[PDB]
Image 1 (cartoon, rainbow, N blue to C red):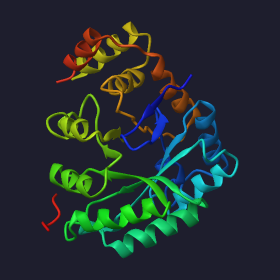
Image 2 (cartoon, helix red, strand yellow):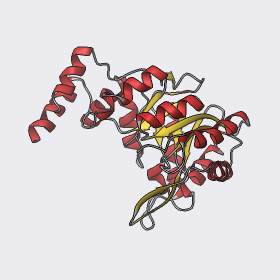
Image 3 (tube, rainbow, N blue to C red):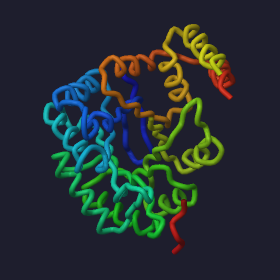
Image 4 (spheres, rainbow, N blue to C red):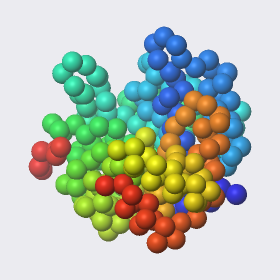
Length: 282
């Protein structure tokens, strides 16, 4: 059965493996028919996953949020933890422009409540940090929304240490979404020690000798290479809840399967040995 974990110290509890909805909305052309989009979420829940991730920016005009919202129709919300995000204002030739004004925070949250067709969001993330607005201000509005019961818990995505320290001072952060895998371990220096001091949950999100090393290691542990890399992340701590996404059921089941792999400390080292922006002050 799907183990469960406390994410953060505020009361949020999730299934040990989350699920990323981003990929289901598709792409302006060849994309996924709502039918099997909802099926994939449904099966996810059947496999015991209750933590579902999306953003206002995924799909087209919140099309991704609308999909999850439709899938919840046939599910017991209340047993499900809905993670969503705001902050990315636009995307284009000049890069990614974030917005973190209190007005934008509230309007985005309400727009997400409506598309998701829910009364509250469990985990509301700042998806990108607005480097023009003091983090205290952005976190100020999020606190209000917690107190009004519009959201329950606050998350950050790819924030600097300074941004994390200062956000958390205003209101406890429940989750930090970040990139983390065998091939990408940068967060281990400072980011991870930080989440562990402040009790913030960590949510990871999305030469041939080396491939063979890995496969030979996955074979020895009775799993697939993908399963093994995932299992490596899972074993990095009780406060670590990765959120792989997929559009196919098979991949989903493969991923769930990674939960059966048990790795000793010895096994973990062998596996990892086989692979060699601030807001303004005040």
